[PDB]
Image (spheres, coloured by chain):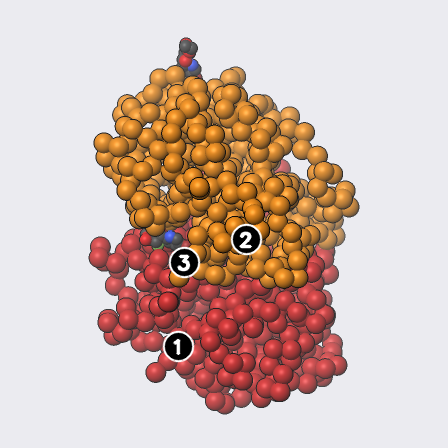
Chain colours: A red, B orange
Amino acid sequence: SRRRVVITGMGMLSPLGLDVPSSWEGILAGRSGIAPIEHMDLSAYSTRFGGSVKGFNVEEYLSAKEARKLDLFIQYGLAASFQAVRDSGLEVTDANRERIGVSMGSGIGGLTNIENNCRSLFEQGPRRISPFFVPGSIINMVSGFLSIHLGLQGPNYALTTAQTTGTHSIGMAARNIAYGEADVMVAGGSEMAACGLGLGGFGAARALSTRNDEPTRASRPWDRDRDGFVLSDGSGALVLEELEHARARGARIYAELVGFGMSGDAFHMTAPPEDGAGAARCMKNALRDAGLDPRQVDYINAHGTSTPAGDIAEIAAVKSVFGEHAHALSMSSTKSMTGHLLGAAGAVEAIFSVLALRDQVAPPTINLDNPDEGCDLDLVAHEAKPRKIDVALSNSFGFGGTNGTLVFRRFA
Amino acid sequence: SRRRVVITGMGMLSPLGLDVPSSWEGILAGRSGIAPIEHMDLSAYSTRFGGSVKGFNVEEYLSAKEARKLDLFIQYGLAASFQAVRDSGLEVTDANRERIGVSMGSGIGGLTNIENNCRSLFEQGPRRISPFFVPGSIINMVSGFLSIHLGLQGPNYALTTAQTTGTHSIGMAARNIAYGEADVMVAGGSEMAACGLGLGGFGAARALSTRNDEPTRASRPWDRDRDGFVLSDGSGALVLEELEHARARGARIYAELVGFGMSGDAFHMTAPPEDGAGAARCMKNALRDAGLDPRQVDYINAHGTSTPAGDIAEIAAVKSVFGEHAHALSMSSTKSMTGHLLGAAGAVEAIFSVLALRDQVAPPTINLDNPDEGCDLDLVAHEAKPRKIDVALSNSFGFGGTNGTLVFRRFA
Ligand SMILES: CCOC(=O)[C@@H](F)[C@H](O)c1ccc(Br)cn1
Ligand SMILES: CCOC(=O)[C@@H](F)[C@H](O)c1ccc(Br)cn1
Ligand SMILES: CCOC(=O)[C@@H](F)[C@H](O)c1ccc(Br)cn1
């Protein structure tokens, strides 16, 4: 048997806002968080825009001294984590601190720090590398710093599964609770890859939209004029909690996490199979995990990256899993507004999936002016769609063919 | 109910050898793999030696076409994974490919590739970044590329928990199998952090031994003259398999994985607590998970990094967990010979713990000339100790205060 897992707190930094309610308001209004990247000479780059976090104030969370030791992706992860723990109302005590752990991940981790220390190393040699370079840049330091700050002694780890990180982090944290290794977990991911090496790295692979003239129209999942994903920064964190533990302290429960699927495509390093066979196995695994018939799904938060191949693979995957129900659910890509937060994508999209359940509304796929060949599902083009949502799926597909699916349900 | 997990295949690159048996021969003979680094000019650096893999031929495993795209840490991880799979005798089929996954992790990932692409960006501009920079550097692409080459469609992920990565990767993969999420997992880790950024970064923290004039004597866990860890490269991979699945196919079983513990110190970003309280919590979690009396433990493969604070914290933890039995078990640090493979340390040390069970011998702690104050356990100083070993424990403790413990026992 297995314990039940609920969501009792959420926290976020995104291109749409510095917390969950500001981000969610932007999502339901179809606002874009995408703009030209400031304070950076991107003249020589084929992409000059992305989803930046605007006006982040790290001194709301950390002292100047502790902030200087930490890459922006760690700052962002800690901001989301502190928000989520505050939102949960949980009180850490000597009686429960061994039962509270952390799994906050990242796809690409501390590129900004690596860039700045490369500069020191190439220009002045190794003796000008910062002493906090390593501990301030390693992906497991959101989990590490959070556990030190709050006194959490539970399972402490970090996933790095590229664009799937945030989905896997949440799913595995939910397993830890379900199988009794923890009663509470803070889970999610963070990313700040808008450095030269990030825009340059994805640019070299020609994976990014180059729609420099109209950045807000660049991210257009399933639209015939899409030309690659939009690179975005931020973080998402959820407080996952065993149901009886949540009920005993009178926690506000947002939703239940009922299903988690994983699969490998075993197909290509960066491209999904055209038929989305891997994504289809992963969704089927997640529904089996939840004991749910495909017909019970109302809402899918797609991976929906705005790549030619990825977007069409997900349509094929959903038609395959859902058959005669594939048109009755609503599926949307909030990446149309946020861009692609890479390892934080799954974290912020799990939060959007929980809020779709709370507010009974499917967020829009903006910029979906001209659906592509066979993109004839209900993709919630342009504007939010109030509807019945009992069950919401959130999908992530990443480099290496690594897939994850979360299944959330309304809690009563 | 929870299924039993056994080890049916192992694979390794280390400073001592290009496979498991050559590395193990070195371990039992007390040989050092530590030597001045040849692959770059380190005259500006305070540490100029480490544990290199010597004479690695990637063309034993991969086409030159594919090898050229991958960071050394990925090449090392694939080599160890291929060795492990071949050693297992397992055949991948349409009937079992959905039930075989991979969890190969890294602490730092493709730092050589990142540094080289940073150099291109700064000297020549973004148009000179490799198109393969991201998929060839990102930590999850051991798991990704292995799944693509062998057709593994089961759970596909990667951990990054700094110096605990290999132990956590093996533990969590064992839980996948235990809980029914897979029947087989390839799990471990790989590392190649020996570039200017890595030696410079750890140097800037003053975490490394600076014994440049006697590199084979540098790694001296629990010795009064120790002065930090020795940086080393390589990979370990194990094929973990559900017991009845192994029995059904007539697999050779090396040993059974009976216990896994995790804990967070919640103390400091880099330093362990002097009393080893988190390490003690982690070992107790693992022994209770294994259903053991602590007196059943015969051998501990320590973390034993050759840091002043780390080594003595481990003695304090072991004395706290095992009481008077702490004087009866044998505990050694193979890092005395291999140095510290960071995210691959737990993976190679899990293999050495399994071979300790197969061959009924405690590997030595070489260089243990003058044991420090209170380091008065059986630390297997200088020479391998043949002895009865039914139960072997492998510990790892990392930045962020993140702890892991694996418990292995003989299988009859
Ligand atoms: C291209 C992907 O790169 C990364 O993920 C890096 F962030 C990597 O994990 C790393 C390098 C150096 C140090 Br210090 C810590 N972590
Ligand atoms: C302080 C944590 O205490 C516990 O009892 C367990 F959580 C245990 O450490 C553990 C955690 C996660 C996984 Br996977 C496996 N084992
Ligand atoms: C008996 C052989 O060893 C000695 O005589 C001493 F040198 C002692 O072993 C020592 C101390 C510090 C370091 Br570094 C290395 N060796």
Kindly identify the amino acid type of the residue bearing the numbered disc 1.
Answer: Ala
Query: What residue is shown at x 61% (from left), y 59% (from top)?
Result: B96
Query: What residue is shown at x 70% (from left), y 59% (from top)?
Result: A268
Kindly identify the amino acid type of the residue bearing the numbered disc 2.
Answer: Ala
Q: Label 1 marks which chain's residue?
A: A
What is the x, y in percent for residue B406?
A: 41, 44
Left or right, B193 with respect to B386, comes to: right
Can you tell which mark lies on residue B2? 3
Task: Inspect this view and state whether residue B341 appears.
Answer: yes
Marks 2 and 1, how far apart at CA? 42 Å
- Nearer-the-camera pick, B217 or A88: B217
Residue B116 to residue A288: above or below:
above
Marks 2 and 3, how far apart at CA? 18 Å
Pointer 2 residue: B248
Instruction: Same chain for labels 1 and 3? Say yes or no.
Output: no
Task: Inspect this view and state whether residue A349 appears.
Answer: no
- Crowding at dot 2, Cα within 10 Å, few <14 / some 14-19 / many 20+, comes out as few
